[PDB]
Image (cartoon, rainbow, N blue to C red; front, side):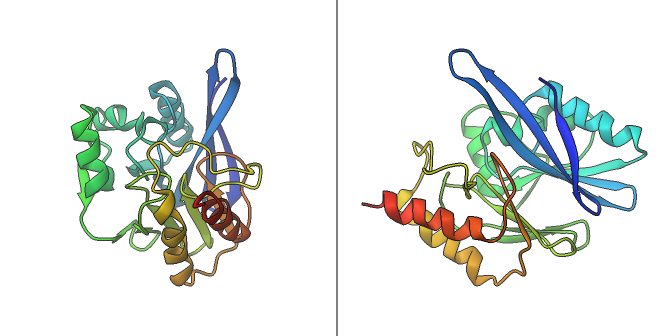
Length: 217
């Protein structure tokens, strides 16, 4: 079941890839493509090399030049495409921590990484922030100031979920404070895109804090 790419605001597309788990069924994973004229930036690669190449043809068939990708945590749902993008001399970015985790697990690493808790791509198009551990030790978020989209990735949970889900790599203790760190940025959020499931509003944030503060005890 192939990549889907759908418009969700001007110059912002939601890309969704799928995995068929034999005995369970189909799960999905979300990234974004962000356009600035004919320059494209990918937030999270698709979940396979094959879906990443489709995403690459989606962009190049439209006359876009993919300038970069940024992966929001070290796991394969967000990094499967890094080797392929590296093979094509499109710059790949992660936090320094995400880069070091990939290296430790023997995985291809990005060609670029940022050291602070804050980083920007596309001359202000994408603002990246490390709010603290949550779903994973290294999860970051992306704020899109024009469209007022917050890409929360796996650090936020859609309303389809009455539970935080997998927590093996989680800091359950710290996951609520990391969200409150995002709230303190005081972003004018109109939409929140989760790593899995449906797009919602800023409400997705309080909703995740609750699944979190709940699980704390």
